[PDB]
Amino acid sequence: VEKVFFVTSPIYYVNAAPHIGHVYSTLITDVIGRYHRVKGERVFALTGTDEHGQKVAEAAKQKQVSPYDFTTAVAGEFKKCFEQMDYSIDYFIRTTNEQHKAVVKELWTKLEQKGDIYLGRYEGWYSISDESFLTPQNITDGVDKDGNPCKVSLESGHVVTWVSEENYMFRLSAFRERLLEWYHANPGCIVPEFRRREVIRAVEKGLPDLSVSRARATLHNWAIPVPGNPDHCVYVWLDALTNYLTGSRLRVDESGKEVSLVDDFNELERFPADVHVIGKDILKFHAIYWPAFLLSAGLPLPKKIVAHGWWTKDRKKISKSLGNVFDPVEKAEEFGYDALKYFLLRESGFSDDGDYSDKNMIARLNGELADTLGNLVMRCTSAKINVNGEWPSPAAYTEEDESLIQLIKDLPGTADHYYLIPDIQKAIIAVFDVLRAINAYVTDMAPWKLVKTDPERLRTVLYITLEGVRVTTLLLSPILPRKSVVIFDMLGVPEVHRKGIENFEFGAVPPGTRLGPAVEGEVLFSKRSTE
Ligand code: MET
């Protein structure tokens, strides 16, 4: 099937200002989308804000302003932040959007007509902060923000409350066997694998029916009314998951504004998502509830859900009051945007709860970006080594020449597989193994000596080096979107060769291609001191 590659981030609660967790999640979404665009594919990358619910409504009561003004303010902060992070997102969705509401009502009605929604009661624990139902097995003792004894989530640590309400219930219990068929039929549908094992384990134990409405007062009327029952509002999560569907059905103008909701998802060829990027904290919603709603509705299921871990700074929690902040924009201004992105994508894989420190950030920037990549780019383009300022024509290749050429020929196939898992960390490591190899080849050949001694040999060494740089840079362009453009400018790679699987091929830029012009003091990544 040939379709728009559809990649999504979670839509984030707007109870509070955007922070690193959100930036990271969206960054992951952005990178995947960026990579599929360089393969020449149509892409629709989606992010947004989850704006209804008790959590958000109460967050706005605390700051003492209307939910409409509050959600709009905070959403504005999310957009401003993401614009500043210089992503390439195709649309920003807000669940307050009127067309989103229509799609929710449409899906709800499908589930009802299917016979999968009945009137019942939920009597059990709820975490408002997580907007999540919990069994007693998943709560424990703790202290509220007074210090008085309460119950809290084992998952999250937030206060839980007992809820006893007549609610509309989705028949999730009836989807146990089909969800199990699905997980087993598509053993790559949840990444990383140990999270796939989590979901299976959980669904194996058994599934209770799920409350998909709440009484309207409980939600302070800040939700979507249940169609046909104005006393009930639709569960914030059923509403929020529907954003993926809504997004697949919106025609967007050049300004980034929704202008039309199509009746059928096929019209736009986006749905279902090829990758839902998420955090591990919201796995059940995406891997259990969502495919269950889609099965009931008769909709296609997503191809992959990839769930990453949580961040710490200096081996502690990120928190304003505890005195340990990590501001992505602040660190980008300090170290650079592409560098910070490299770090967050390099320093941790999706199975790990990684760690930012200034020390280790500077170690990677200097180590990998400046010495390994940065220096290689400057040398092979320098007037000292590349005296004619062009891509030379290679002479005959030695076996050592060819060992390196093989590594470069093999790199795209390997990096491709990693980006498709997806495992962005592994893709980066693969590209830098090839970069380390190029540097060691250069050390061996000492092109600086060859310039005097053997210009004919230099032609070969220099051409291999330029091409190795070009290919590695191409495959890193989704990680270093701005720096890759600079690198390609220095190399003098024509625009047409900066994109497309055609240009993953060794030798796509011809000898004789001229290098771009130099500047007095220019440097790709400048070293920074340690303390
Ligand atoms: C459909 S994704 C919803 C995610 C939720 N709003 C959160 O911030 O965790």
Image (spheres, rainbow, N blue to C red):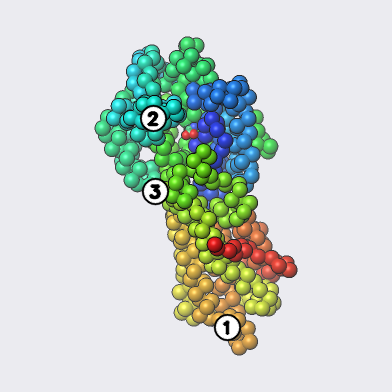
Mark closest to the chain's N terminus, 1 or 3: 3
- State the residue position of label 1: 457
Left or right: 491 in relation to 29: right
Q: Is residue 179 above or below residue 125?
A: below
Q: State which quarter of the image contains the C terminus.
A: bottom right
Q: Tell me the amino acid under the disc marked 1.
A: Arg
Which secondary structure, mark 3?
Answer: loop
Q: Earlier in the sequence, mark 1 or mark 2?
A: 2
**Which residue is at a point 35% across and 46% down the rendered structure image?**
193
Say which amino acid is labelled 2.
Val
The image shows residue 22 at horizontal and vertical percentages of 52, 40
- Mark 3: amino acid: Ser
Asked if the residue under mark 2 is in contact with the one under mark 1, i.e. CB atoms within 8 Å, the reply is: no
Q: CA distance from mark 2 to mark 3?
A: 30 Å
- Numbered disc 1: secondary structure: helix
Q: Mark yes or no: residue 527 visible.
A: yes
Where residue 285 appears, x then y in whole percent? 41, 32
Q: Is residue 97 above or below residue 367?
A: above
User: Mark 2 or 3 closer to N-term?
Assistant: 2
Q: Is residue 96 left or right of residue 253?
A: left
> Which residue in the structure is indicated by mark 3?
351
Query: What residue is disc 2 on?
Result: 143
| Residue extending furthest toward the front | 147
Task: Provide the secondary structure element on which disc 2 rests.
Answer: strand
Residues at discs 2 and 3 in contact (Cβ within 8 Å): no
How many badges with numbers are in the image?
A: 3
Residue at the extreme left of the image, as rendered: 205
